[PDB]
Length: 329
Ligand SMILES: Nc1nc2c(ncn2[C@@H]2O[C@H](CO)[C@@H](OP(=O)(O)O)[C@H]2O)c(=O)[nH]1
Image (cartoon, rainbow, N blue to C red; front, side, top):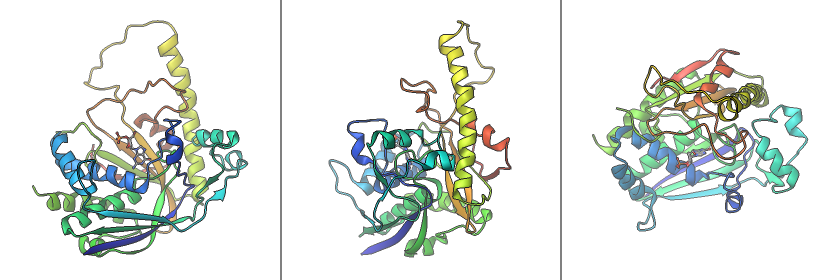
């Protein structure tokens, strides 16, 4: 009768908008249960061949499906009340470009509240199986350390941290609920890769995985807002250059492109960023997911909605010193 309990707290503003997703599909807002499931496939998947079939077998065997009951019961409870959103703060705090789609929804009045930094949430994992309560907790751990939840969370919203917990599974694995140093970060990542393999038993894949991903940090900043604002300056220059670039390519003079001297040269990979707390101080966190399946830079929708790609790392690392936490690449 296993049970893991956690209290997580927002580091950056968190927008949980599952509700808007039926009318507006641009408003993808992954929940905690949602994002845990994702991170599981990115831990496990570091061990499966390009064997999507088997990964789906294990994934459904843990989290459940339409033809299966879950072996783990994930209970999430807000402990804070949503606060009224202050549209004045995007100009004031210099987050006007990264969180543009939020400000837009705010001004239209589609959203009026949000969980501001400090909001707490209780997550409680229960399972009769030990193999399962270990995999579920690594997923939650991965979510907090490398991921995010909510609308625009791959751009700094929904960054989380653990403030109190009662985990017999992290104790067992020799893991922490916080990072006192960067070396702690590095070591735990390594540890999570190794332990995940064993629990399961026993050439790059098509899906995103933790094994094949770069993780970088920088700072510390004075506060969380100073970090976010750095991303916002960097993104703005990215966006300026990007717009100029794609009007050249798509609508300018027709030119015949040359095949790259290296296979899959212009296939740039997804990049999420956020805010991690290391030693009590705020760091910018960046993660790049390298895989084989393709993802076009070019989608039918406004270019301020286009996914940020790995070629963005320049616009941070050329402007302030960056530290590599995880080098798989
Ligand atoms: N953990 C996490 N996953 C996300 C976030 N945004 C999108 N995703 C997941 O990653 C993918 C990025 O588009 C999405 O589809 P996918 O499930 O097909 O991989 C989604 O499930 C996020 O902010 N956090």
